[PDB]
Image 1 (tube, rainbow, N blue to C red):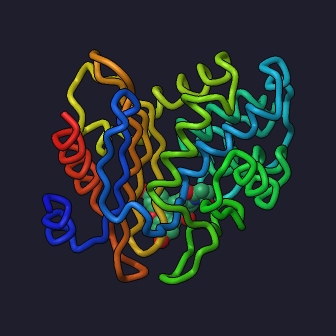
Image 2 (image 1 turned 135 degrees about the horizontal axis):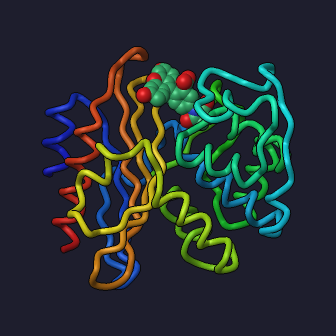
Length: 256
Ligand SMILES: O=C(O)c1cc(N2C(=O)C=CC2=O)ccc1-c1c2ccc(=O)cc-2oc2cc(O)ccc12
């Protein structure tokens, strides 16, 4: 209803699933509606990379050229002369949403079909990887390639970061990278009080798709895991990061 009102204000469709891991209390709004997952899939991709490698194996250096570079290469364009390690590539993918870094990591785990297989193996029957960066964002309404839902993304994000799809050292690396995300200050982070730690990964795609997935730690107690997904209407629609910030405030009010 506050969520209804936000849809009205931003002329958008919202998808919200949040779970308090301390109480199992939930806040749901279209929790099972599909949205292009966009770059949020970088978080699940690193999850799988970490599963498929020792911490030491992440030190393997990957070489590439301007030919492995795509539309958006913030860190990856600085190091084509020397290459980057897998650890450095996981850092750039998660924290700067480097599309090139994501594509090389995808290559290392075996491309979209193998990502899907590993996602099915951990219990995710909804998230549907099909394509590399950036083609995956171009989703028309009614298609299901490169989509997930807010319920699925929280369940999968929780499985890697918080439960037993990874051992503790690797969960620590995942959560460290995601706590130090640079792309998310005006989204979920802006809807949470200061002093509350947030680990997040953002996405943006056509149809004004604007997403954020996060783990949120209140000083007091167990983490909350949250997906805020949104889309419009128009293919060339703009989004407004404020809608995510405000949705996040409503979620925290409903659980506090
Ligand atoms: O670069 C792009 O193609 C683009 C690529 C991805 N991307 C992923 O999210 C996972 C791999 C990948 O290609 C995600 C979002 C965008 C992106 C947009 C994509 C299509 C278009 O409809 C508008 C986009 O607008 C964006 C805006 C941002 O601020 C930041 C980003 C975007």
